Amino acid sequence: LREKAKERNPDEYYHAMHSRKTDAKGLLISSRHGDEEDESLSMDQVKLLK
Amino acid sequence: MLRRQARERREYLYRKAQELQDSQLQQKRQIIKQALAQGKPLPKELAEDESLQKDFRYDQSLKQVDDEYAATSGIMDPRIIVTTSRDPSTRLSQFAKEIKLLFPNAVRLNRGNYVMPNLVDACKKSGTTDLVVLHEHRGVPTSLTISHFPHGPTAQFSLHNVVMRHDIINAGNQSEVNPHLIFDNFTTALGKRVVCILKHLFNAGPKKDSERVITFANRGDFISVRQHVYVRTREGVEIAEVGPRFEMRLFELRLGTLENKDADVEWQLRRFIRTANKKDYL
Amino acid sequence: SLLPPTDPFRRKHEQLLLDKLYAMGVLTTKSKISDLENKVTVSAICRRRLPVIMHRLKMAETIQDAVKFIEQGHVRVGPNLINDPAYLVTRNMEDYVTWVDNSKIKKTLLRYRNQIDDFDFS
Amino acid sequence: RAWDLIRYRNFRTFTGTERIQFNCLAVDPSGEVVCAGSLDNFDIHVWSVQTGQLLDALSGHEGPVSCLSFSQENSVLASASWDKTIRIWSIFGRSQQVEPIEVYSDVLALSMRPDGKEVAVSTLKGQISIFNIEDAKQVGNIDCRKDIISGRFNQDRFTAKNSERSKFFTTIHYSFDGMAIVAGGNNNSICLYDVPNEVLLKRFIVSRNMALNGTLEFLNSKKMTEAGSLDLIDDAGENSDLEDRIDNSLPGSQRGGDLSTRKMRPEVRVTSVQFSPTANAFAAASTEGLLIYSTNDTILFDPFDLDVDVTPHSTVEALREKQFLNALVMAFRLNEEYLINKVYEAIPIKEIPLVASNIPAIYLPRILKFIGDFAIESQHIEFNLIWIKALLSASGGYINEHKYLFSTAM
Amino acid sequence: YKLDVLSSVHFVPKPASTSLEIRVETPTISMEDAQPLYMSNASSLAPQEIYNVGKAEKDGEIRLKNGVAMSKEELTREDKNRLRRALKRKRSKA
Amino acid sequence: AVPSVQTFGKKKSATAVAHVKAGKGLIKVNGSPITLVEPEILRFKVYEPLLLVGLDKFSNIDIRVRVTGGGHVSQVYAIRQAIAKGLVAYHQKYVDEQSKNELKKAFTSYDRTLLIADSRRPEPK
RNA sequence: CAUUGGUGAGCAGCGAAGGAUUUGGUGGAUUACUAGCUAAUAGCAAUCUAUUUCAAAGAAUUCAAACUUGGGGGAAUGCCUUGUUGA
RNA sequence: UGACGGAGCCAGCGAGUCUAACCUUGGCCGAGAGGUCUUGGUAAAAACUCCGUCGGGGAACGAGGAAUUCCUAGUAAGCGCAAGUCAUCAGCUUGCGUUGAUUACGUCCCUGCCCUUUGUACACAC
RNA sequence: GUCGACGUACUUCAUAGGAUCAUUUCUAUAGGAAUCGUCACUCUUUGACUCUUCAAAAGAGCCACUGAAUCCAACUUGGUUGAUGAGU
């Protein structure tokens, strides 16, 4: 792992960078509920659930 | 320049790996060069083998410094920095100074707060060929590492029976001329390697008249170093010693520089092996 | 090859041509001298072309996207940028191929790693 | 390689030490030291002219050297590299000390003042940053990325307002006065700035030639169709002759070799810009040759310090009643070339020295400029040489003080 | 040449060269390029290259490099010594 | 969205991230108003990117900073570099380029290290 | 306490017989404007043919002729060049 | 060239199911080994800013003579934290950050130390 | 410190027998199985075109005139004598 961090190449671009996020402290934030839409709800669904 | 240095590291390690894969093809090409010359039959392998025989014209055209130094062995005189550990002591500052005088083309340097990656970087970027960092123990020095910079080896030596010129005798002051070198009783392949590192640390192709030789005697795993000045009398040579006397001893030989701490290890001294004490260069 | 072996013209010209082609990058190693007729291929020259280098350096995802980003104009070699997918990049220019400045692809890398600095307008 | 220019010879060729590809040159005033730097090695090599060996390899950049120059007064070597830095090396005289300057980004041309106190540096983000060398400090930059006309190529798929192929100046040069910078680049425009006021004076367009690529701003939509663009088909088949059909072109060979060893149309660019050390002109080497741009006082009405009573009729009257000093200064105030010539030849040889003594300080540079412009192509060599002897003789030391306003005139 | 043009010149150069070549005395106007004016005049060899001074073709003389020649007879004996010393060390190196 | 611009400042081992978004004119540092940046002698080192360019340019934006690393003096120099780069970068983005130029001339004529990193990279002599 | 993350319910403010995003089609510009067709010194444009044919002029390389081929070995039979037997 | 309180305020390296004392006074249980509890004795971020307070030591000592050594920028010097890596290191050694300067940056005059005294290479000059 | 002779100890080599496929009929063998001018219908396999996802990136650019869509404002009609939501 330390050798990989040494040849990181700080110009690499992969396309899923548009979905995945990070911290202010650097290491990445992964959600506990799975998908890109599986974060939070809407008002019509929440009303029906209530 | 960072991306450059890294790219040639990646390349040269690769091309060495290839080399260790084609030593066996070296050997299959030597056989045919014997058998064409003096008529001897070939083995079944080389006999049936046709890639090789089809391109044994080109390879027939085919056919010592160490490899990290081969690029600039005789062209450029080196540039060395000699530097202390961190918060030194008065005795160590003297020792560093007179080591600087021992090597021509060495510039002393005081470390306070120069973290090691910044020291390696700044030397690399300014262009200094190699770096000597020295460690004490209450005044007595005890270690010395020497490391060669465009990504090349570091030898660590431990150093033992020390006497200092400045503190023994003020009979005068050192010649500071290109010295002669003597390398005695270095035989094994590792021994050749250590000869190569110390020898290329020294200076340019010195004159025939220079009266300052420096001896490095391998006596039994312990490298011993002394400085000498002389004359030629009509019956013999009158040798007057100068400079510090200390038994050096090699105990590690990494391949990166001295920051790396995970570079590959060519040779490391192993103390707790069952037959440690029996051999030499082990 | 048809000249005789112990002949310094032959030795000089093959050693010199190997070092030429290896610096260009169309053959990888400089030891075996049979590689001239053996491992010199249109495929080796193609894989020194420009989009493939991005793909190998991981500036892309696949050679189709490296080609696409070159053609849309995000890649530069030094100061001057390349629209040209068929550019052949010698080893020492492989050091210098990079993203252009203020492209949206450069901003995405930085914004992800969380190091945009807008004074650069990166 | 060094060249003589009286007997026409290489008297030396300094070489490398491993043969790298050299990309910029800089040489001392007392021409005994030559530095060159490449895009290959990022170490400035320094050779000595006489003994053709190399004194030194001044090292310390991290990234290839893009320009070098010599301050010709104080003799310092200021160099600049894609490092994003400038380094001012002081090579002669026990020092060997060096001083770096960080610029914001990736510098790519340099220009030293005549005076030797200032370095102007043209970077990749589009400024000209003008620094002071004794200090290390930035005494002014001028922001340029806008007033630069980058066109669209036919082989482009992106608008010219985004095409950052050419939004910077790869060449720069001060005046010989210390007041203007001409800069020129990889684009269709040469821009001429003024250095104190930081505001530009004119923008020149190198060409309008739709058989070059970077030259239109907006292409034509009648051309682009379903196939693709329409100037980009091949028509070598249409040609009636074998050598006009044959199309050698090694694929993607961006700017080397002969013109049809590439299948792309030329791009307008200014390869390098300089001022003129004697006249009011400048010259810029570009795709179609060296554009030489120059000036006429004999067309523009640019008077100096006028008043109501100063007409061509009045100065002629001042001649015909012989107040030759006043007639001359009225000519210099009105600033009209025929008039100055007229009085210049009216006044007589006995009266030349008193007039030359009594001229004013403000009009001295103009009279020198006029004598130069008349002098190289006229015939009155006694008239001109009597004038010059009187002018230097009576006002030498003043010129000696103000050495730089008079660089070109003298 | 093809490989330079393909690689869009950024190569690595040749190793080296040093090869002798011959130049002729010729006037500079006869050297330059054809157009109504001219620019330079002086001859293409230098005066030192048409007559340097070297050792005298008799034996009775010693001739130095600054163009002064002296017979063997008309030197005092100490000077004959000292000139022998000078030629001794000069040809001792070369 | 919001008009928002992020810049970074840096002295020996400190760091300081400024987010500048258009708002009503507050300045805060680690969740406290700027008027309590602590070492109290160097408070005017922090106030000088404000009082070199007048308060109104900050009357119309909401600058909010976070630092870490280093000691007292280093965090002071990181805060003011980040603020100065923040104000001139926002001005290039969401107002005119001319006022970008006037800002940067002010900060550079007074003290160029409001804008560029003062990196005392070593020297082997 | 933040949110510089969504989805909504509401004000202040703006505010002339309404407003806000998205998209199809055609016209004009994108280079500096001298009109259409033909067998063309003229006719036609409602039509070129029931004068549209004549006369004159017009025939080197006696065949220069793939400047047009990825590299290495070859070629039975082809092709090609040089010789040859019988007409 | 400061003591003593409070109160604010900021680091960078360390992350192997492995990390760590010695005696003692007695009670209980067990056949013993030992087990359980009880009792006493000895070993192991700082600077900085802020607010109030204060104004010789239990016989050797009040910042260290002559001499010599070392030293040019995150340098000298202060200040703590962490590790312990096949040699060395615990009477300690190497790292890591944190505040951070005065004075030269010239000259060969002194003590030295080298060097060349053959333009040689090709202009021009000297 | 070196090569010769001898002594021992390892390492490595043959391929026979039967079949089918290779000649634009026939690979040599009679022990062998195929010569037909099309009409529908079912299931299956690859491809175009149009949209699209991971997941984005770039717009041959401007004005005019004209249609079309979606959401809010407004008005009209049905609506607590039950609107919309909602698994027999």
Image: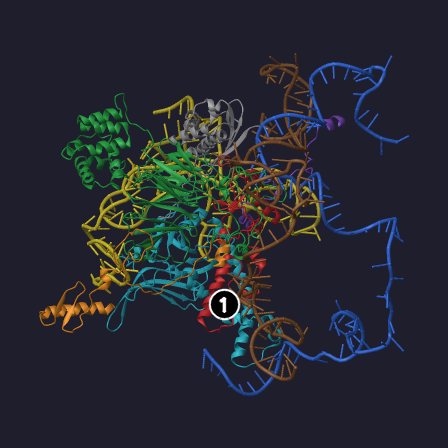
Chain colours: A purple, B cyan, C red, D green, E orange, G brown, H yellow, I blue
Towards the viewer: D409 or D15:
D409
Residue A50 in view in this figure: no
The three-letter amino acid code for the residue at tag 1 is: Lys
Q: Quadrant of the C terminus of chain D?
A: top left
Left or right: B200, with C45 as reference point: left
**Residue H19 vertical position relative to residue D305 in the rendered view, above or below:** below
Q: Quadrant of residue D375?
A: top left
Residue at 53% x, 73% y: name it: B30
Q: Point out residue H82 in the picture as x, y percentages from the top left corner.
A: 50, 44
Q: Point out residue F17 in the picture as x, y percentages from the top left corner.
A: 51, 33
Residue E4 in view in this figure: yes
Q: Point out residue C70 in the picture as x, y percentages from the top left corner.
A: 56, 45
Residue under numbered circle 1: B278
Towards the viewer: B202 or F7:
F7
Chain letter for mark 1: B
**Residue F73 vertical position relative to residue E39 in the rendered view, above or below:** above
Towards the viewer: H9 or C62:
C62
